Amino acid sequence: DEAATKLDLARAYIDMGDSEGARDILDEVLAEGNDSQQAEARELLERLA
Amino acid sequence: GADEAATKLDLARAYIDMGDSEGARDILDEVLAEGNDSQQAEARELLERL
Amino acid sequence: GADEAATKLDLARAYIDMGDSEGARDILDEVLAEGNDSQQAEARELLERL
């Protein structure tokens, strides 16, 4: 699943302090993921905000 | 196809973030084969910076 | 040290979700050598699941 992969990649960016990169990837999840994946993405986005 | 290239572009840039140019290189090669015109152009730019 | 291992652990999870177990194993091999006890433990758990 591409959305689930991007969620992990977003977490990897967050590890490296690349917040802008993580943000853009989490936006891809919003577009690609199912409802629960969108939820997870928004959770991480808020944590950045 | 293009949705796989989007994933691989994210992966490759993660490798650049880490400083692994060689790792990025192998993946960017797959973006060149999989991605749309826009994604191929991004891959080419990144490859030239490596 | 533990920051790079944490990043690699998430990258490994990404490879697994891509169905790329071979790539995940190569990355996890690095976590085993680089990570703290907790990170190593997670790498082992991921490897045994794969």
Image: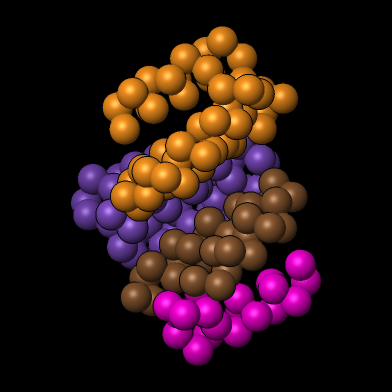
Chain colours: A purple, B brown, C orange
Marks counted in the figure total: 0
Can see residue A15? yes
**Against C8, is C47 above or below?**
above
**Against B40, is C9 above or below?**
above
Image position of A25 (left or right of A19): left
Taking the magenta stretch, the answer to whether it contains residue B34 is yes
**Rendering coords of residue C33 (x, y %):** 63, 22
* Residue sitting nearer the eye, B13 or B32: B32
Query: Residue A21 lies in what quarter of the image?
Result: bottom right
Taking the magenta stretch, the answer to whether it contains residue A20 is no
Residue beneath the point at 56% across and 72% down: B29
Residue beneath the point at 42% across and 78% down: B34
**Rendering coords of residue C11 (x, y %):** 50, 42
Query: Residue B6 lies in what quarter of the image?
Result: bottom left
Identity of the residue furthest to the right in this view: B49
**Rendering coords of residue B49 (x, y %):** 78, 71
What residue span does the magenta drawing correspond to?
Answer: B31-50
Image position of B48 (left or right of B24): right
Residue beneath the point at 56% across and 10% down: C37
* Residue sitting nearer the eye, C9 or C23: C23
**Against B48, is B22 above or below?**
above
* Residue sitting nearer the eye, C29 or A30: C29
Identity of the residue furthest to the top in this view: C37
Identity of the residue furthest to the bottom in this view: B37
Quadrant of the rendering where the C terminus of chain B is positioned: bottom right
Quadrant of the rendering where the N terminus of chain B is positioned: bottom left
Can see residue A44? no
